Length: 139
Ligand SMILES: NC(=O)[C@H]1CCCN(C(=O)Cc2cccnc2O)C1
Ligand SMILES: [Zn+2]
Image 1 (cartoon, rainbow, N blue to C red):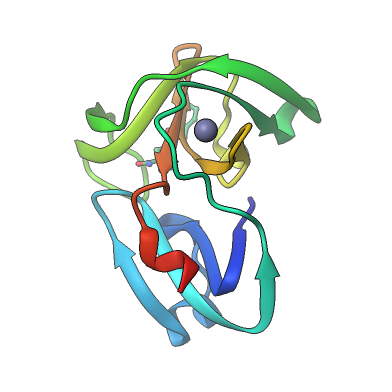
Image 2 (cartoon, rainbow, N blue to C red):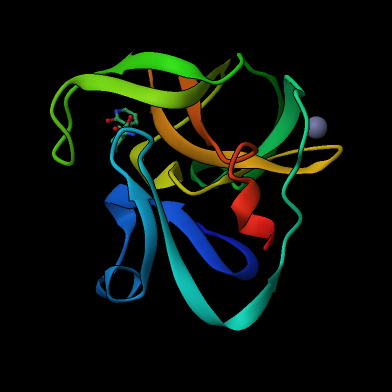
């Protein structure tokens, strides 16, 4: 689990969005596994606006943060799960590292701020849903 709070927005994995997230829906993209809902309170997370390929992500299944090198956002095939059939997920970044289903929502950070959130895992790889291109999150 986990979310990003910036301005009047809450960014979560689309497959983990709650009834309240859907009742306050701003934007959602199934191909990216992203959902954004509106919030009453102000968020103070800073979104990174960069092309970094190194950062640190939080891994709840280990209660640890890990420094990782990660690929640029792209269309990557993702195996079927109880949330989605087998499909290509867009804006996804891969790194070598530990990830279990409950790790989705862990934030990936670089020197500039929030890069994205854990969205896929398995085979010793961790995938992150990029959020750096969503410039509207800051207004
Ligand atoms: N973005 C998605 O489509 C994800 C939806 C939740 C399940 N997904 C995973 O990759 C989680 C996982 C981790 C480790 C081993 N197996 C798993 O299934 C896919
Ligand atoms: Zn950066």
